[PDB]
Structure formats: C-alpha cells, structure tokens
Length: 132
Ligand SMILES: O[C@@H]1[C@@H](O)[C@H](O[C@@H]2CO[C@@H](O[C@@H]3CO[C@@H](O[C@@H]4CO[C@@H](O)[C@H](O)[C@H]4O)[C@H](O)[C@H]3O)[C@H](O)[C@H]2O)OC[C@H]1O
Ligand SMILES: [Ca+2]
Ligand code: NA
Image (cartoon, rainbow, N blue to C red):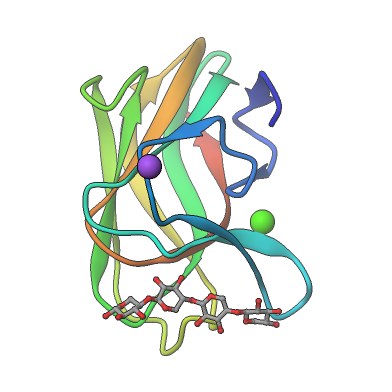
C-alpha cells in the first residue's frame, strides 16, 4: 500500500498500511471497485503519512452498512488525537454506499490516520476537506 498520500485526493480504504483485525477482508463493490469489510468492534485500520498541508477540518467517507455504527478518526496512532467521529446509520444494505461526512479538528502537516470501528461497515474510500 502507498507509503504516503494527499489528504485532498481520494484515499482507497482497501489500500491500508496496517490493521489489528483478524477478520477484515478486501471486498468488491457493485461497480467493480474494492473496499474493506468483515470489520468488527475494536478494529483499527491505519493509513500512513497523510499530508494535510495547511489544514483539514472535514472527513468524508463512502460507506455501506445495515447497522448503525461509528468510526473514530484518530491522528498518529489508535490512542492519538481524536479528530472526529463519523456516525453512520444504516444505508439499507451492505452494498448500498452513501457518502457521509463529519467535522474534525483542524489538522496540518503529515500524520498517520487511524480509523477505529465500533462495528460492521463496508468502506470504499474517503477524503478530507480543507479548512477555510
Ligand atoms: O462483487 C461484489 C461482491 O464482492 C460484493 O460482496 C459483498 C461483500 O461485502 C459483504 O458485506 C459483508 C456482509 O456481512 C457483514 O457481516 C455481518 C455483520 O453483522 C453481523 O450481525 C452478521 O453476522 C455478519 O454476517 C460484513 O460486515 C460485511 O462486510 C456483502 O454482504 C457482499 O454482498 O457484493 C457486490 C458485488 O458486486
Ligand atoms: Ca475503494
Ligand atoms: Na490476527
């Protein structure tokens, strides 16, 4: 998976750098994309060296799930700064994807990003939004 990435271009969830998960799989999506799934509560997924430049204050992800779930966005490590939490309610099926966004605290410079999952969700991709 790439050693570094730009916060303001699509990041593919399946191109993660490390995970604690023993269940996570790379899955297909309806339009022959890929994502991650078979995620459980407590699972973390790390993406290395994301460059936020002069700042990001939002997070958007394209996700599918049948259960209300939440995803913490942390900087640097699983115990690093909580940037925000994305609350995801059911999208209607494991294959019905929805872009869902949340606010985060302004982050600048280069940081690993850790997604922390409270339960099952399929994730295709994500991207950050620049501060104003
Ligand atoms: O070609 C594409 C197929 O690859 C794709 O397959 C889908 C792959 O993802 C699957 O999503 C799974 C569904 O099960 C979830 O686990 C459930 C979580 O809740 C629990 O209560 C329950 O016991 C578990 O079974 C898992 O988290 C999730 O990733 C999806 O079902 C497949 O259809 O489909 C699109 C094709 O074009
Ligand atoms: Ca993807
Ligand atoms: Na394992």
